[PDB]
Image (cartoon, rainbow, N blue to C red; front, top):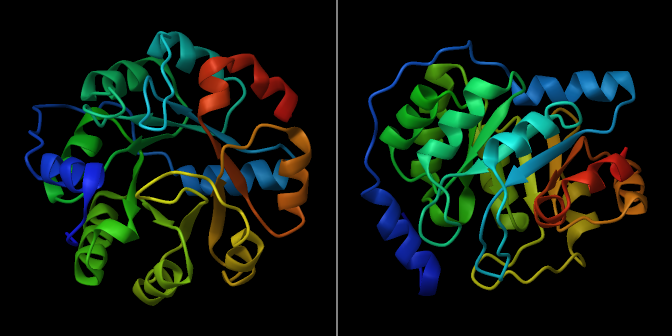
Length: 246
């Protein structure tokens, strides 16, 4: 991993040691990436709803994972489940319960830094993972991206800026999440948004993570070529806001 400071350093350190579980998927791998393109083809807004109990920026919510899931399953293109333990108070048990209850694509949101976390995600029933450019060395990224493809996943690559993008297009990314979070502070800043998205080629599925909250922002981002929308906080507070985003 890169040398990092603050909570990020600790979560990465913490993530190396994350223990992996004995499991059996279960259903077959479904493609979150390809689900996005059908919803585009169908003129259906495509929201990836995130499940998280806590966040470092201050999010603090009680809500049952399965009731969240069973509910989003009718509305949402996919679900992202935090399974990081310390700062977001997730775990593998949230992924487990969520996969047996629903039949839509699931992304496992964590700080992926080694192979067994990809094994656990596969084994626990996740359809894909997130890989974060700012935490990995370019070689680590290339390697973890291949590994997940050996299983059949097309992993989201997560980027914050043009350097991140230049690395991801070099390794051959097909599925990109554009974060507006400052990774060390977080801390949303969208000044750089339009410009990043304008540089990604048209054969890469693009997803925006952005504390979106209003319908009209979704509309403005369509106009720039974005495929879909990763939405956490507001939906974790009121799952019903989803109906407004269609």
